[PDB]
Image 1 (spheres, rainbow over the protein chains, first blue to last red):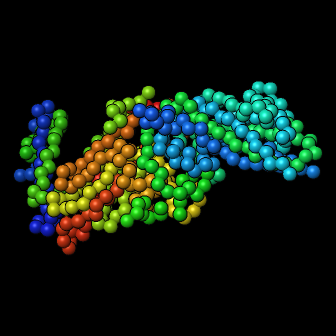
Image 2 (image 1 turned 90 degrees about the horizontal axis):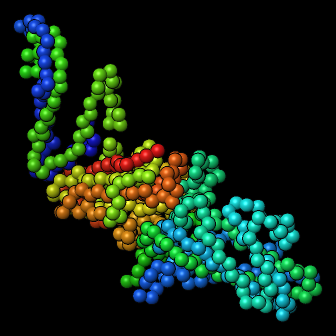
Image 3 (image 1 turned 120 degrees about the horizontal axis):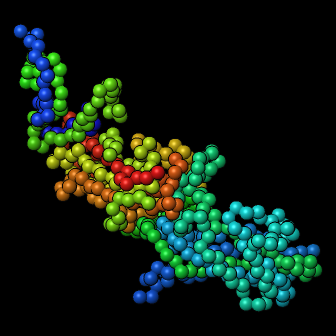
Length: 39
Length: 207
Length: 49
Length: 175
């Protein structure tokens, strides 16, 4: 959430963007196979 | 160096109460010890947020007739105890309670009060209301632990035909002072003896 | 990769991590609160929750 | 500074105040802002981009009885209680206490000057003359923040709202 509003200089637009990324950690485990529904 | 030690800065005996009453062809005092009745000592004291001290108090009478060496009683009444109704009252007799009788022509009476509060120091400012919960009538900042009792005084021999005014002057030497949390100086006139309000107003120094 | 690989399997265990990244101009700043809702929680409706 | 580690005997982040070139200043009262014998610490920073100009004095005052102009009348509930929403300084130059802003540096003070630093932090150890206050009805410290020099820089759409973000932790609080 925008806890402050944004602040930017006169030379840079409000077209400012976040990228989000994810992974599992070292501790991860997957139990037992069942074929994927996406294809 | 001299009055640079805070006990010497503060320890000048302040005339904290100055009043009169007559006896002629009611008329007793009950003033609580708070140093807000006189403006110089108000400011000089307000430079510190908390102080712990004994108080010496000295009582000096004076007379304008219209000398009779009367007996004066000073009594100290603690925080929130009963206080008398008139020159005559059972309270002036109180068994469990400090008092001094002195004659007007003796050199003036002195007492020490030890440091007297349920809090560890006098909090010279306090911005709260109560120790448990607040009602509408509980005024902002008048802390009960700062009540410090009252000095109560009467003429004991007041039957006299002769007609006059007793003046009394009360001098407090706060003594053996320990102090904490200094403050920015109070740079503005004082409207009242309770809070700090005002009405120089918008520019503290000249051009 | 998390959601593709794991789709081949019955149930999963262990921790994740997000990484966010901000594509801004160097002179630009702001504070975003991020907050996380553990299992069984309600959605935080606004910044006070 | 007062030289205590925060001590007895998780932060909270207030919504950002929209500063402007004209703004007089803001305050919060502790514990009131948390809604307890404690070492509060307060950590305040500007969301200010490098073109911006102006400066804040950050001060924590003990037992700060807010006064008022033009009456002997004492403050009401709603004037002194403000929670995390906080209150304005009606007269910053008098610090509302009839005392000079210029002398407020006797209280533990820090500067946000936008050249040198956009961030400042203070430790507020317990000052109460009772050992553990427990009622909702007193505030031992007031955090105050005042624009000593007016906010400036930027143009047009930037609209001078350059926010202040305030953060508080009651570090080492016991009950």
